Amino acid sequence: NNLGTELDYDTFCFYYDWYGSEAIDGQYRHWAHAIAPDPNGGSGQNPGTIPGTQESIASNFYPQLGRYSSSDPNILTKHMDMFVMARTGVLALTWWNEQDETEAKRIGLILDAADKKKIKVCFHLEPYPSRNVQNLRENIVKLITRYGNHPAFYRKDGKPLFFIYDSYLIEPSEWEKLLSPGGSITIRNTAYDALMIGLWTSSPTVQRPFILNAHFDGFYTYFAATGFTYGSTPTNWVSMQKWAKENGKIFIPSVGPGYIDTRIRPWNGSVIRTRTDGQYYDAMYRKAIEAGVSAISITSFNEWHEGSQIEPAVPYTSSEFTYLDYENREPDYYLTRTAYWVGKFRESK
């Protein structure tokens, strides 16, 4: 087929499976959430919590699917249909090393649901407690062993791919042991080799030698809010891609439709980026495509706390809060707009 509707498998969309319902999970997990104290406020703050009721959830937006469970097979089916609409071929699953049966179950359901729609799954490895290169190797081994034969397990030219959040918190001398072909616990040339994509945060002075000395295969930027870091300032992307190509590295800039997390972080208004009927999303996606990259990541499918989601949202006013919504656009606008940009990306690829 040459219909311009096919999934793109160099487009990665960051996906969260931490939502719960009382019925399926015992609690409206994540819909209920702590409110963070202001880092520059006093000692003795009592910020409180968001209860996760129908009226009051931990997002400035409101999901079309309501307070859904990430464990609900029928929610998962609808999410995969949304991925198909968006033409996003890879679901990049947040992985917090929860070490519990409920998460193991969710990962299996997600893989199965993805495969029904030809979607692929890769893992976004988060900074879990005591994360280090040894237990990272152990976890990489477990993931590849457990899921590597699943038809939905993502591979690029035969290799799995991992996004590593906050990679910069581990010294390059530690990464070398895992990621250099001569590293003492190397995954290179083993059954567990993978494309390792680290989080580029700050200036090239710092990030260039880090990426080289740590032996990352590439880098991504994550943050949906333009200007939050050097990496998430789209005017830097041309230069970042130039360096990536010069150094045999894979650059996967992250694009988002907007940002707002003030329900859970009321003091954090400076990071707000307004959606303006999709123009923000367009501008950011345009910059990624213009930089001439080979892959793009999307922040996010459903990080509802951060207001970066492309998942459909609906107008909602409760007694507790008046939510933001997609303004002059329909609930599925960010999905269909994603499909539009995937088309432009593929056109110049």
Image (cartoon, rainbow, N blue to C red):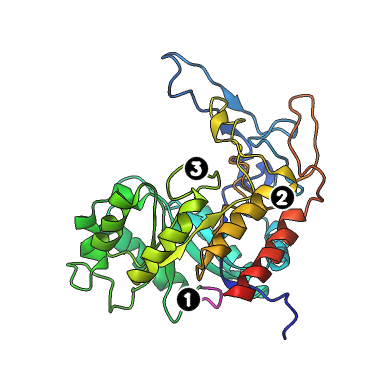
Q: Amino acid at mark 2?
A: Gly
User: Hey, which quadrant is residue 307 in on the image?
Assistant: top right
Which residue bears the numbered disc 2?
A: 278
**Rounded to the nearest whole Å, what is the CA distance between mark 3 and mark 1?**
31 Å
Read off the magenta span.
Answer: 149-153
Residue 245: x and y, percent? 39, 70
Q: Crowding at label 2, few (<14), some or many (≥20) Cα neighbours within 10 Å?
A: some
Query: For the residue labelled by badge 2, is the local secondary structure a helix, a strand or a loop?
Result: helix
Residue 52 colored magenta?
A: no
Q: How many marks?
A: 3
| Quadrant location, the C terminus | bottom right
Residue 348, disc: none
Task: Tell me the distance, in whole angstroms, between the alpha carbons under discs 2 and 3.
Answer: 18 Å
Relative vertical location of residue 13 with respect to residue 36 in this rendering, above or below? below
Q: Write the residue at 49% across / 48% down.
A: 233
Q: Is residue 181 above or below residue 219?
A: below
Q: Is residue 312 visible?
A: yes
